[PDB]
Amino acid sequence: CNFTDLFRENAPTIMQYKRQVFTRCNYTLLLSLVQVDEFVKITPEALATGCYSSLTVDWFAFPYAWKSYLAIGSADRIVRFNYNQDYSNPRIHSKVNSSVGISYSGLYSYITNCNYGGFNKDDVVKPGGRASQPCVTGALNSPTNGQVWSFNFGGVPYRTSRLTYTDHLKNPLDMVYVITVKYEPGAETVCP
Amino acid sequence: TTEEEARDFLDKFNSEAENLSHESALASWDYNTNITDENAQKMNEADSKWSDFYKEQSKRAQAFPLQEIQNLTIKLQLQILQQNGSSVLTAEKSKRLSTILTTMSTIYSTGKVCNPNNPQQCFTLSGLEDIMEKSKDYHQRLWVWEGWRSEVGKQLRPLYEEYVVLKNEMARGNNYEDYGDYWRGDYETEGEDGYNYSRNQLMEDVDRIFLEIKPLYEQLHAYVRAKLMNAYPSRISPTGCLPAHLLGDMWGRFWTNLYNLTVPFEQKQNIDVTETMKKQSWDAEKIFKEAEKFYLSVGLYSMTQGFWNNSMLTEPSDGRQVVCHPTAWDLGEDDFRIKMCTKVTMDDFLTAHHEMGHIQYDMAYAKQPYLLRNGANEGFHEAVGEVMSLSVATPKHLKGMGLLPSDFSEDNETEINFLLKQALNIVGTLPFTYMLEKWRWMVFEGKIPKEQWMEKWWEMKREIVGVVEPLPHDETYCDPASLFHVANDYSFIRYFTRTILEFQFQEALCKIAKHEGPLHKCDISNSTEAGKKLKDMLELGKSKPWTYALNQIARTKEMDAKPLLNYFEPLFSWLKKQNGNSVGWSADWSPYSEQ
Ligand SMILES: *[C@@H]1O[C@H](CO)[C@@H](O[C@@H]2O[C@H](CO)[C@@H](O[C@@H]3O[C@H](CO[C@H]4O[C@H](CO)[C@@H](O)[C@H](O)[C@@H]4O)[C@@H](O)[C@H](O[C@H]4O[C@H](CO)[C@@H](O)[C@H](O)[C@@H]4O)[C@@H]3O)[C@H](O)[C@H]2NC(C)=O)[C@H](O)[C@H]1NC(C)=O
Ligand SMILES: *[C@@H]1O[C@H](CO)[C@@H](O[C@@H]2O[C@H](CO)[C@@H](O)[C@H](O)[C@H]2NC(C)=O)[C@H](O)[C@H]1NC(C)=O
Ligand SMILES: *[C@@H]1O[C@H](CO)[C@@H](O[C@@H]2O[C@H](CO)[C@@H](O)[C@H](O)[C@H]2NC(C)=O)[C@H](O)[C@H]1NC(C)=O
Ligand SMILES: *[C@@H]1O[C@H](CO)[C@@H](O[C@@H]2O[C@H](CO)[C@@H](O)[C@H](O)[C@H]2NC(C)=O)[C@H](O)[C@H]1NC(C)=O
Ligand SMILES: *[C@@H]1O[C@H](CO)[C@@H](O)[C@H](O)[C@H]1NC(C)=O
Ligand SMILES: *[C@@H]1O[C@H](CO)[C@@H](O)[C@H](O)[C@H]1NC(C)=O
Ligand SMILES: *[C@@H]1O[C@H](CO)[C@@H](O)[C@H](O)[C@H]1NC(C)=O
Ligand SMILES: *[C@@H]1O[C@H](CO)[C@@H](O)[C@H](O)[C@H]1NC(C)=O
């Protein structure tokens, strides 16, 4: 299993977060390479070993101090218009040394509001699903000051707003890696 | 060739007017749903563009005299444009009149009344209205009512006096006898055969309606008095008028807040569907979609795709501020919208249909020339919406929508509570509207000396509605101007008209629907014949006299109170049993005369 891309130079934003699915490959080292600050259904030691049908990991930049509302039970904008973590198939907070190519260039932002139609229906993210492109496009064209702007996509009117977290820049940075393991029997293709 | 040139003129006007109307209407809509200092000025500039256009076109319209033109369609559109309005006055009088209008409006809007027994406490009008519709304390109610009249009435009287003279001179400049006559002209129509209605005829039919509704009001008055007399013991005579400050309304227009004191059967519960909607997990979307089906079941028009995508139907969660108050919009270019902040409540289930009803009418006359894109009369616009509202409220509809138990039925006690609650909004409001409109008309006409304006106002109120003020006003007071629609340039007859038309239309649609029963049980849906007949009238707009438009539904030429009396027929009979010989009132009674 090749995890180079998890600690590679191009650290993603959440609005456009990245993920990689591993299958039919051989996967401790990932945790040695970065500095872990915290560990949060499956025990991380149970996750660390054993054979899985499939292993899927997503990652994005995110302040450690903001972890309070990244968890289940949160109804924050950082959950509904940002990243809705799935829990159906049984989260490491870490920082990355500047000695590791981690460029962290550009601006890091998130969506705060995204709705549409005459009923102002919230275009909320499905678990394991990214923000809708209409939401992504409106956010890209947003003033970044939090002001809500009007957009029209496919004839449907949208209201969208964007804010940043690009002020939280320390040499180690703050990143979150979420590993989900599918333990369905009969496959078992991802082993240590 | 005057008519031919006039036609080309009007087609050019109508085309540009639609484009300018769209820009203004859109800027206004966007502002109301997105309050920002950037949208503020934007809307006005758009409004000015239309205004500058309308006046240039007015001058052009006057080049096509109505005497030479024979085609009535052309004459009506030109007649609308061929009006000088304030541009008959000198610059000083025109500017002075505008200044007075702004000042009178401001005095009302920013008015407040302070507590005479405790200077620390003081309420703005919004707080004073809240007291009038809720408080049962005779004392609190009295100082807020009296205070409002003293605080604004004595500042507006002088302005209104000068305002009257200026409005009359303006009307003379526009070839009317006075400003009352100018307003009467809104009901005047030109046509052949029996489709001809005069300005003076309006007064005569209004008096006729008053007398026809009068006996229902007299029965309601005696009943209400008998109950308020116990609520406020030793304050009201067994026979006599009601105290103005105890009517549940700062201006004494509606008696609806008295329902809890005057309820026919205290032991009976009313119908409230709010609980059912919550149990059934309704949304705002469900309320509006059902509103569309109601009208499709009547047989009118569907909603457009633009309606569903662009209208602001609920309050946003975005952070932007919006204006909440139910309004039907027409932005032109077949762009129809409804603006409201819908909640899952039984009241909004009726309001959504009401606003939807306005759109149904607006769509119907969309095929008319720009200038004629209105209701036949302002009373029709509102009356049609109200008829549809009653049809939805009727329990048969609620059962059809699955909002009531199948084992639910109404008894003859429930029907009485329903009708009286309606009477407090419909019947008790009529002689008020009539009294106030007639008084102003005499003021503008010049039948009452300035020093007698106040005396005539209260003498009429005692004889027409049976309402009395507990502490006498020397004369400096101008109580009528304490009301929004008197301080501002608004007419009230439309409300008198709206109510009578509502019933004429409801009854006529019921017989088409073949409802063999009471009008309060009659619904209009699932009767496509009634739908089609209503379609034909709504489509007309101002291309025809309102007497024609009325005939198309009710088969009559004039206003008729009989349908109203019919609707409340079983209420009237019950009130007789309750009132006995107490029916009517003594206009010689007044709290001040007690000691
Ligand atoms: C509530 O009301 C406010 C006030 O009107 C609205 O604010 C406006 O929103 C529109 C978008 O709907 C903004 O238009 C965009 O402006 C961008 C430039 O921004 C800079 O320059 C302007 C001055 O012109 C500054 O005010 C601003 O602060 C920035 O410095 C353009 O780049 C955008 O271009 C896009 O559309 C054009 C269409 O022709 C395309 O060709 C482009 O490729 C691109 O897609 C656009 O023109 C407008 O500037 C905002 N006004 C102000 C004062 O900020 C809110 O949107 C409204 N909210 C809601 C929900 O209705
Ligand atoms: C608007 O006012 C103008 C005057 O400013 C009216 O035009 C005058 O009408 C009288 C009566 O027919 C003529 O004797 C004058 O010669 C006209 N003056 C001008 C400059 O044309 C005009 O008729 C009024 N329009 C309306 C609708 O009242
Ligand atoms: C008439 O009495 C009813 C109660 O039967 C009042 O309804 C209540 O109004 C308050 C708001 O002031 C609500 O919080 C309550 O929940 C309502 N109660 C019920 C059972 O719905 C009604 O307001 C009274 N009418 C007037 C004019 O005061
Ligand atoms: C409502 O309907 C009931 C039932 O018909 C009426 O009560 C009846 O009145 C007659 C005439 O006095 C009596 O002979 C019956 O015995 C009564 N029945 C019952 C169950 O009491 C009632 O009077 C009607 N109310 C109104 C206002 O019309
Ligand atoms: C990061 O750098 C510090 C300072 O030299 C070092 O002590 C730490 O072990 C390094 N951590 C990782 C994961 O390389
Ligand atoms: C909104 O309008 C578009 C046309 O621009 C139409 O395709 C779409 O179905 C409409 N959506 C709704 C909910 O009416
Ligand atoms: C009046 O003008 C309309 C067009 O606006 C036309 O259809 C109608 O036939 C004309 N009537 C007469 C009598 O010329
Ligand atoms: C109209 O007819 C339908 C059946 O097509 C019925 O479900 C609905 O309840 C009826 N409407 C009313 C008000 O009864």
Image (cartoon, rainbow, N blue to C red):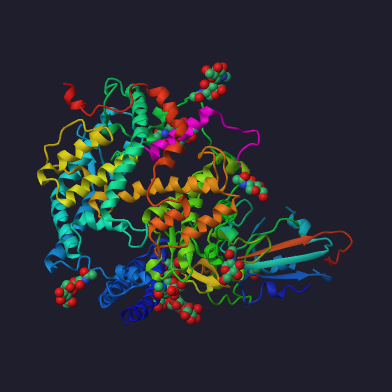
Q: Residue B466 colored magenta? A: no
Q: Nearer the viewer, residue B20 or B585?
A: B585
Answer with the quarter of the image where residue B10 lies. Answer: bottom left
- In front of the other: B307 or B195: B195
- Asked whether residue A146 appears in the rendered view, the answer is no
Tell me residue B304's x, y (percent): 55, 65
Of A168 and A86, nearer the camera is: A86
Q: Is residue B386 visible?
A: yes
* Residue farthest along the front direction in this orientation: B193
From the viewer's perspective, is residue B372 above or below residue B358?
below
Q: Is residue A111 left or right of residue B483?
A: right
Magenta segment, which residues?
B402-428
Ligand 6 sits in which quadrant?
A: bottom right
- Residue B319's x, y, as percent? 45, 59
Residue B259 at what x, y percent from top left?
Answer: 41, 32
Residue A163's place in the image compared with B240, above or below, is below
Q: Residue at x 26, y 23 (%)?
A: B235
The x and y percentages for residue B424 are: 39, 36
Q: Quadrant of residue A111?
A: bottom right
Residue B411: within the magenta? yes
Q: Nearer the viewer, residue B591 or B299?
A: B299
